[PDB]
Image (tube, grey):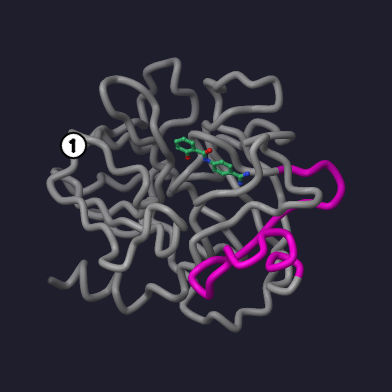
Amino acid sequence: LVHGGPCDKTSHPYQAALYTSGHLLCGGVLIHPLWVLTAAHCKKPNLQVFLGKHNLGQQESSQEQSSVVRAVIHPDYDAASHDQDIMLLRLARPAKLSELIQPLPLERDCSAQTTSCHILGWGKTADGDFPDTIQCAYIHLVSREECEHAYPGQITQNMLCAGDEKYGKDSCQGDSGGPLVCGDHLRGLVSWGNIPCGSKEKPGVYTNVCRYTNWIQKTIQA
Ligand SMILES: N=C(N)c1ccc(NC(=O)c2ccccc2O)cc1
């Protein structure tokens, strides 16, 4: 996450860190004790999910680790266009909830008026390094027309754009699958955007979670 700052320790209990071969890969969102929501392009072998983490460089009393027993990629996911970039991960062990481990409710209404949004993650910072401490930034949803002009013919109804006109606060590599939180609900998932990272002109592109509330419910209830 570029041009942001360290999160408040108690403000991200739904944040998951996804590992493969002992390295941070992506973010994720805890949405149910047994399920983590992430981006489909984060699919790697033997995924390890860490909940209750703030600083990845230290062991923390609140952390809970789980292997993934099931990875459910959306059936219409298209790697090339990042369309329908969503995946559900079933945890081997249901998450032990605490003040630092809690699910985040999803936004079900695609017509939600809120634009008081924030992003979070352990992705690349402005200096190019990977932070040990989780980063946070407030961003705003960008109109569909403006996003369509920024990325001609790349924006589907399954994507939502967000950014910041002032400093270009944006998500980056490693933040993928992480949450775009609007009005204390999950509104989007970090999917793709401008390289180098910066949202002043080209906003970040997020999976539009409200479009998937039926598919999520059917997967969890299967
Ligand atoms: N500007 C943005 N909002 C943005 C840019 C890039 C990524 N992700 C990547 O570049 C990436 C690259 C390799 C592997 C995984 C990734 O997520 C995520 C968000």
x%, y% of residue 122?
A: 52, 31
Q: Residue at x 29, y 37 (%)?
A: 49
Q: Quadrant of residue 85?
A: bottom left
Q: Is residue 116 above or below residue 110?
A: above
Numbered label tally? 1
In front here: 12 or 201?
201
Seen from this angle, which residue lies furthest right?
166
x%, y% of residue 17?
A: 39, 36
**Image: magenta residue range:** 146-169
x%, y% of residue 11?
A: 56, 45
Quickly name the residue at label 1: 67
In front here: 133 or 155?
155
x%, y% of residue 51?
A: 35, 38
Q: Residues within 10 Å of mark 1 (few under 14, many from 20)?
A: some
Q: Residue at x 64, y 31 (%)?
A: 6
| Dot 1 amino acid type | Ser
Answer whether residue 76 is magenta in the image.
no
In front here: 158 or 24?
158
Answer whether residue 159 is magenta in the image.
yes
Q: Is residue 180 above or below residue 49?
A: below
Ligand 1 closer than 8 Å to the CB at disc 1? no
Q: Quadrant of residue 213?
A: bottom left
Please identify the quadrant where the N terminus is shown: top right
Please identify the quadrant where the C terminus is shown: bottom left
Q: Secondary structure at mark 1?
A: strand
Left or right of 82: which side holds 70?
left
Q: Is residue 72 above or below residue 75?
A: above
Left or right of 174: which side holds 77?
left
Q: Residue at x 15, y 50 (%)?
A: 70
